[PDB]
Each structure stands twice: as structure tokens, then as C-alpha cells.
Image (tube, grey):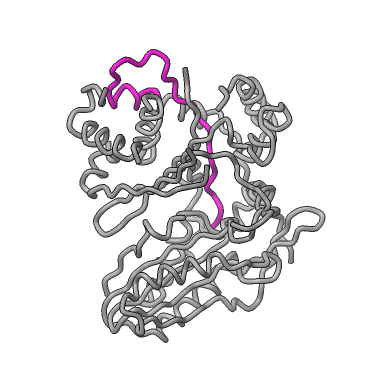
Amino acid sequence: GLRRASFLQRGAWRWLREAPPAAAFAARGLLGSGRIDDDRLAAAADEVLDAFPLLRVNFVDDDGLWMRTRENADALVRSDLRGHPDPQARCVELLRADRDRPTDPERDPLVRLHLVRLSETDVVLGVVAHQMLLDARSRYMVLGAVWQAYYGRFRPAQYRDFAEVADFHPLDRETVRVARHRWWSRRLPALPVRGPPETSRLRVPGSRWQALTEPNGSLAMAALTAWWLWTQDSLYLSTEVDLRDHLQLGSVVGPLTDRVVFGVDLTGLREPSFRDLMSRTQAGFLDAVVHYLPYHDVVDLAVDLGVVTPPRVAARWDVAVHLVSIELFREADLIGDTWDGTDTWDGTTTDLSVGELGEDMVIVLDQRRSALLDGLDAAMAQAVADPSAPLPH
């Protein structure tokens, strides 16, 4: 009973194998408020852990990468933080702590569900998962499924098992694969050449984010980030893509998110507007999407052509842009050393992520050298006010 691992699992395993195990983990959570039966919710979690054999999967690195379905889940952790004056701040520290805990991917549960009670009305349902099992979207799918089971609304047939698409590959045809490999082989050598990590945050009113996003949400970010770095030829960025929407794969719980590398051509810009940069950002992104090649396959290729050297595989695209009452729980805060430690930094110098916080969006910036966030803030206001008007000189 050993299924072969998918291409995104194989790809991530190439760098995750020598990285600290906690690097593969992420934490998200849903906050429930009202009269909540803990035992009923705990039973609901077990039901979901059962219905999705993917959640009970361990990996076997021997003669290739393989998936192994564990019989017993042993993944439901129950905590109570009522003794703390600020239960919500503790719940964040709890999930972060469990996220940073070293996990044996061949033995231990790689998807942990946390049932954390904060008060007499508030309960947080959190998930701490290995990225080779659950991507960004799948984490909330699983969390949503647990609450569905709580009300008896969970139907497993509504979801599509990952087993059906584990063998799936966007480049199944060889003639297509060769063409994509060629397209990137010609462009990788031409890519232009480009301190401790510090975090800065910019809270954006939800209304501001919607008017900017709805017109692609991370594309407004990519355009404006590229713009500011231009002000301080072309600039190369990295962003994720959900293959569910792009390739019309079903509502599948599993790893179906990949990274694409695209370039924004900033050549002739003089007093550019949001439309100007949006046009050039979209042209670079769609060009990369049309000629899609898996990020791990791109990395391997760039290494052979001597463009980059491990582990600095992202040096030539060192800008990353990401993305009873029930609401998201501190998403902005959940979105994430030693002597002679193993250096596995990919070379990304500007990391930009966006997470919810109340009815607001929070932009979390990770840099390796503030003025950027004041720049984005002004540029965003301008982009909504008049996308044809020149951005700040």
C-alpha cells in the first residue's frame, strides 16, 4: 500500500529533505464563538481525519518518494487557555510552537488539528500541516470540513480525493515538456544579476484592499512592489499559483500550489501610473503561466546552466509575493538561530505576504537589506483614487 508521490511533492522534497523539518510546516486557524460542544467538535475532527486518508500520510524516501497511509490518526490535540489573561495571544504562540516542533515525516502525524478553548464562548480550531500534504487553500478546506461535520453537513463525496490527481502532471505530453524546457533554457541565462531578516507590517483597511484587488490580488502587490524597488531594464519576481483554478482540477484537498517566476519590464518608465505597471506585470506573469514549468524543474535547470548555485537558487528572482460565529483567526500573525547552523536560505531578500486581521488586511514584509511599506501605502491609495495618474515621484 504505497502510492507514488506527486510532482509537487517530489519537487518540494528536493529542498525540504535537508532543511529543518519545521520549515515544511504552516499554521492556520478558525475562531468559533458561541455555545460550542468541545466533545462534539473533537468528534468532528476525528471524522475528518478519517475521511481524508491524505491527512494520515507519511513519506518513505527509498527507491524514490512514496506515500504511506497511517491507520491511526493520533493528530487531535486538545488545549485550554482560560487561565491566561490574554488567551488569543497564547493560542498564536501555541500553534507557532507546535509548528516549530521537529517532526519525523516517515513516522509522525504531519497534519495536526488543534482544539483550543480560549473562554466560555471562544474556541480556536487550528491546523498545523506539512506543506507536502496541504497547501494554502487546503488548510482552510480541512478546517472548514471539521465545522461542517460539527453540524452534520460534511459530505466526503463533495470533495475530490487527491489520489485521483496524484499522477497528474501539467506536462504529461513529452512534446509539451520539451517545449517548456526549451523556453526556459533560452531565458534563464539572460536573467539579470541581483543582513538578518527583519519584519515590518502595514495594516490596510479591508475596503482599500478590495477596491485594489477586485478589478490578481497578489498581482497588484507584485506591480507595486516592483514599482517601489524600481524607484528605491527588468525585475524578476516569484509568486504562487493554485493549479485548481488554472487547470480546472476539482475541489481537491492536497498539494496543488506551485511557484512561477516572471519578469516585469521596467525599461521605458517615466512617471508611470498603476495601469502602466499593471500592464507590464500582467504581461510578464501570463507569459510565464502560458509557458509553465514546475518551479523545482526550473530550479534544477538554472543549476545545470550554472545560473544559480545551491542553496541560493532564488538569487535571480529574489522577490517573493504570496497569496455559532466562525471567522479567520489571527491569519496575519500565523503567517510566518544556532551556531554553525546549516544555511538553507534560498536568496530571497524581499518577502511579501498578506493576511487577514479583523475586517482588515495586513501586509507582512520580510527584508534583508519600512520605507517600502510607506511607499506601497501611498501607491495603493493612488491606485484606487486614479489608476491613470502618475504614482509618487
Residue 358 quadrant: bottom left
Farthest-out residue, front: 339
Instruction: Give the percent coordinates (x, y) of residue 381.
Output: 21, 36
Q: Is residue 199 magenta?
A: no
Seen at 67% across and 48% down, the residue is 15
Q: Residue at x 60, y 67 (%)?
A: 110
Q: Looking at the picture, does residue 182 appear above or below residue 209? A: above
Quarter of the image for the C terminus: give it.
Answer: top left
Q: Judge left or right: residue 234 versus residue 189.
A: left
> Residue 261 at x, y = what percent?
53, 33
Kindly identify the residue that appears in the image at 22 percent across and 23 percent down: 388
The foreground one among 293 and 342 is: 342
Residue projecting furthest to the left: 385
Image quadrant containing the N terminus: bottom right
Q: Report how many numbered discs are placed on residues in the image.
A: 0
Magenta stretch: residue 277 in it?
yes
Q: Nearer the viewer, residue 198 or 377?
A: 198
Front-most of 37 and 93? Answer: 93
Judged left or right of residue 119, residue 251 is: right
The vertical placement of 43 against 270, above or below, is below
Most extreme residue toward the top is 268
Q: What residue is shown at x 61% (from left), y 71% (from top)?
A: 109
Q: Position of residue 380 (x, y in %)?
A: 26, 36
The magenta-colored residue range is 254-280
Instruction: Decide if residue 253 is on the left or right side of residue 53.
Output: left
Q: Residue 145 in the image: x percent, y percent?
A: 43, 68
